[PDB]
Amino acid sequence: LEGSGRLADVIAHVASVPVSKVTMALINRLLKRFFMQEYKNFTELQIIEWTKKIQDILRMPHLLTVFRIDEDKNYDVDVAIL
Amino acid sequence: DEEAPHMFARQLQYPDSTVRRFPVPEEKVSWEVNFSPYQPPVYNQQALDKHRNPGGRTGIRGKGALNTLGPNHILHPIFTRWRDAEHKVLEFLAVWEDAEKRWALLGGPAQPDEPLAQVLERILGKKLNEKTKTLLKAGEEVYKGYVDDSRNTDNAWVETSIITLHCDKNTPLMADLNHMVESSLSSHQPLQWREVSSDACRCSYQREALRQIAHHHNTYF
Image (cartoon, rainbow over all chains, first blue to last red; front, top):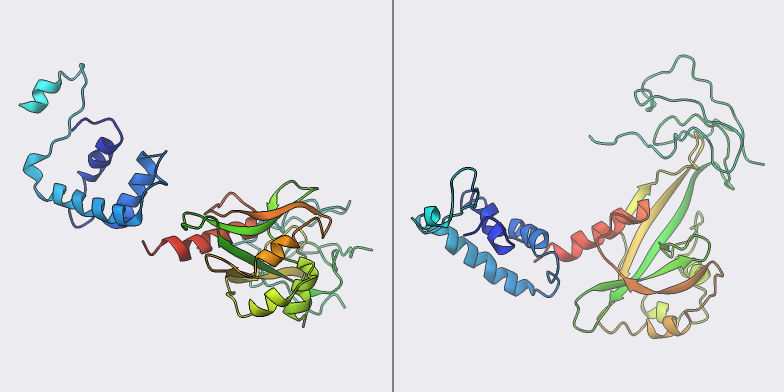
């Protein structure tokens, strides 16, 4: 995952806390915060679907990696893939 | 715990007057502690020991722009409904004064022992109260108690009771009231069911009321 975007910033902020900590209020707060426009068009049931998808993504931590491209610290896309 | 003293009642200059309130620090606000040189001037607009302010010391003595000493009460009913048919947003029949140009509430001065039907007829301009007769059993009890205000003194203060009546999707008692919705009270030149929100950037007493309405509504999902 890229460390700059809108849904990529959601998982880049969720991937610090443990799995128990995340709730439906936190993801609703982050969706209001990152999708500034078009947040309104979302159904609560669709929010209930994402808020299960995101914990099933966070369940296996050895397939999920956030990187951040910066040439000063000698870090690029190949480093993240490797 | 936080913001314990009242802060709109200790403005150094009294509103619409030349008199100045006494200076009162934040430590000596409450009635428990004693201020040794405490001597506020007494200047009633146009039995001053009958009551005590529930908030605290204020540095102004008398009856400041009020018909009575003690509490002056104002009821604030909010006639709310849905905005669209698909229930995507909410709305409230708020007023917007021609002098202030701000979306204010429609709530008037509730007298001591005032009937709610005739007071709502005065505050709404009821040429048709049969809709409010069928909607008389609607919702209420949003908030109740003390209101910080510039007008508060040591003797007189302002208390309010917030009530919110949110109708159904159709709101059958709203068609006659919207047909009777014109420039009746002569202060609010527009008056319609503008879209409600969770606005804490509103009128001071009304912002917590809208936040409480949103905390009621949206918390379930």
